[PDB]
Length: 206
Length: 206
Ligand SMILES: [Cl-]
Image 1 (tube, each protein chain N blue to C red):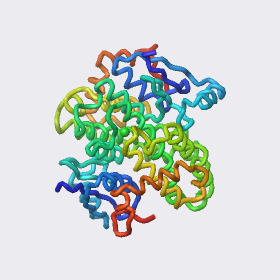
Image 2: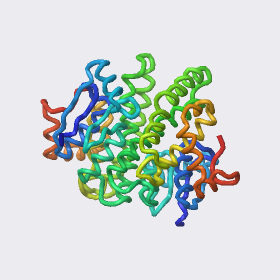
Image 3: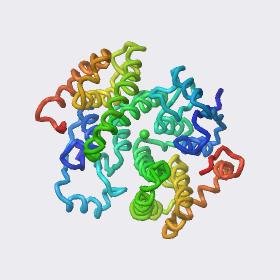
Image 4: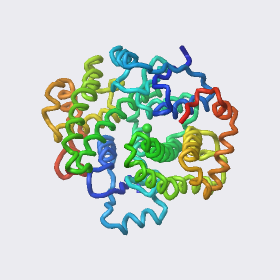
């Protein structure tokens, strides 16, 4: 199938950034949900999971695991990875910061309830004082609609996804970043993104 | 300077994989060690650290942070990232597995002493039963000297580095993987790698 096939639980988890990037690229995709231990064991026994873990994406004859490998391939394939290696260096630097903050926020519910408060205060401080200032500064410096190269790249999508999660986590964290507010509304208005934001899409709930 | 400039503590930590890749590529580099809080604050105040953290590498007019961004740029620049995006997909999938295991092993000393035993047993199980079998299988399947494309790529260097750390951590973990033993000796014998393995190089101690 030329539709990529996404193997994961029926949940956001580690697959959601790949759903976002495919949706932004206008690429229809199929999901095969892991609903049982037998589902996972079959993928493992069939040799489909190089390190016995999901996300796995079947695409272009490959069985790709590791979300960073999956995202890199999708971004290159659909021209969302910039035009040269210096542009990719900016995209990667920006993207890695976003993934680090996203990981901290996701880790809050996997962490035991008695440490969730302490890691929540830390995640909020890092959001307000380390990560969002860096991206506000990028947008303020060049004044362009997109993070890199004055055109849509993968990291605009990664940032929108993060901004949506911040709004779920604590909407007040966004109030002091006006260029990021405007960015969120702009990227949300891209036709493929608008479609993915609508109820009924493959976007997964919190 | 066309020598890249590596900003970090005088320690392996998160900079060592970049030292390895530059050394394997035959690229002379300069180190500027953070020896004081003033050193770090200056980098931060001067706007050199996008997310206020090191590693940072000055290269080709850029101030690159996030080790994955740094490594991606160095690999592309010095032709250690394969020849097409499908080859990069394999390189990335392999590399991400290696980084995940390396992180677990590094985390053992940062973790408090009273949990080091439990995470050590887990790291050893993952080494023996998840990660090293995957790479033994890659080498066994194609029987070639290198992981990807039958030529040296970044991930051969990442794997050698991991194999050296496994040998420090618990040398018995390697005994059942004969193709990985042979791989370690082969990659160690590359002229640029031999040089980096010699006492007196910029390779950092444990
Ligand atoms: Cl990457």
